[PDB]
Image 1 (cartoon, rainbow over the protein chains, first blue to last red):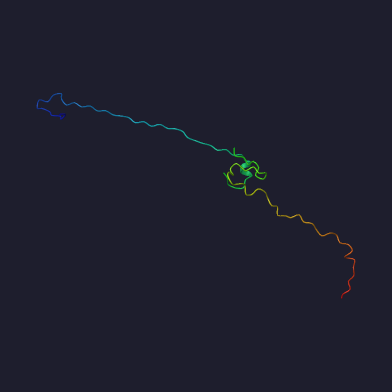
Image 2 (cartoon, each protein chain N blue to C red; image 1 turned 45 degrees about the vertical axis):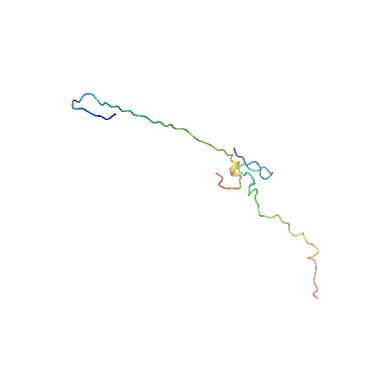
Length: 50
Length: 51
């Protein structure tokens, strides 16, 4: 039914169109921290606790 | 803040959790405090007679 059958007299027939979509993506932030007191590193059994 | 607390008196250090504790908690000076011989009179005033 929808075949572009074009005759011999031509004319404005069989016109088409075009589209386009778009994608997306965002950026988030992460992070964490830990705490220590100097004594807990100076007076300690293990040398390289850090 | 993980603090050293006091392992000697019983309080476990913060990083030492569950069944653990500090494993070098003092210092051995390794220099014993010994006493010398008591002063000895009587003994050096003595002649000997061999048997």
